Length: 142
Image 1 (cartoon, rainbow, N blue to C red):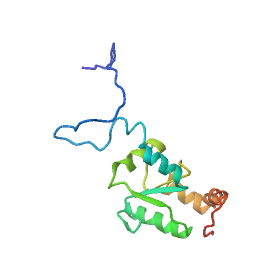
Image 2: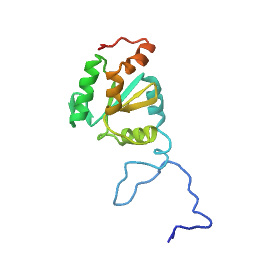
Image 3: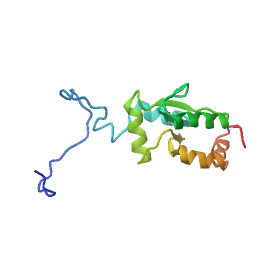
């Protein structure tokens, strides 16, 4: 037993699995929840704006997930979208970069901006529009 104490602590080091877990599957890997996949690391740098949702923007699975795509329509700009339920890389990245995830959730230029409650303040203040206009982009504005 650990008993809240130790000596020589069993020293572990992060590398991605070479074999399966037995009779119980896992969605997260020890290297993967410490470093994002290099194809996704280039993708977040290749996009100017990224969002992830309960489902897909044509078929949302939550009311708050729908409300975000209607707020993207209120701005007249839509951004590059991923389903948190289909691939566990999405729920892993959002947890690691934002600390505490609340979906649907938004990122700009590989940096964390906010959940729907926060995006709402930024959109309702024109503060979201300041950054997208600094990126040379035209939105609907209110």
